[PDB]
Length: 10
Image (cartoon, rainbow, N blue to C red; front, side, top):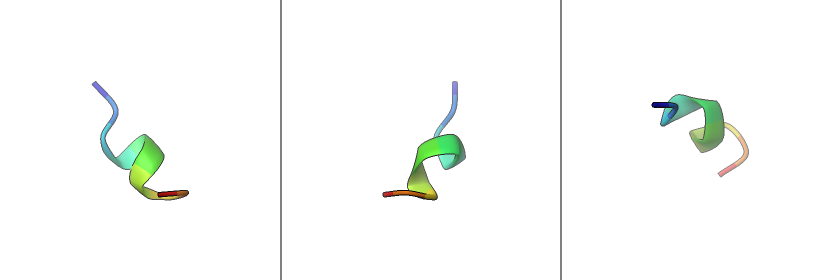
């Protein structure tokens, strides 16, 4: 599960 792999651009 990637939650920080997206919070970067989000």
